Image (cartoon, rainbow over all chains, first blue to last red; front, top):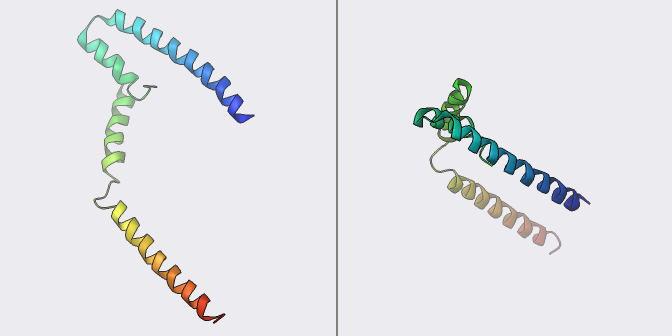
Length: 49
Length: 50
């Protein structure tokens, strides 16, 4: 039953990880400075999936 | 940004602050002494019946 519950949770995470990737790409297309963009990465440096 | 920059400083330490040279070798030497102790116990258990 847990194996089925994992597959359900894994699918929800794969949907969530695609929304994060889309938010990061928006936020990178914004700052428009090598410094501002390198600062963004540092925030998500521990939040790489 | 400062809290995350502090975490990176703490992370560098946590990796290489509690890190000690020769760790896996010491664990193997501890395992060897337990293996020899068990080998001596089974011999003593063989001597009891015999």
